[PDB]
Image 1: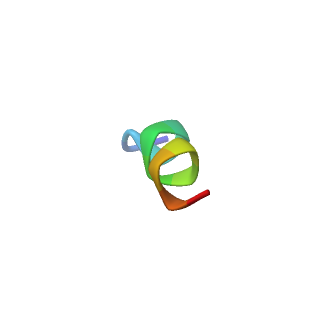
Image 2: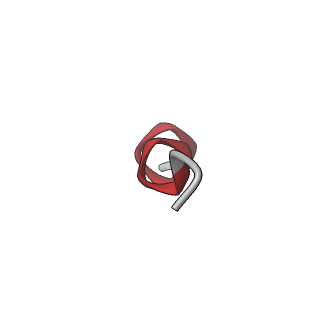
Length: 12
């Protein structure tokens, strides 16, 4: 994952 979920939440 690599905190990917956070990158998606921040991106949007």
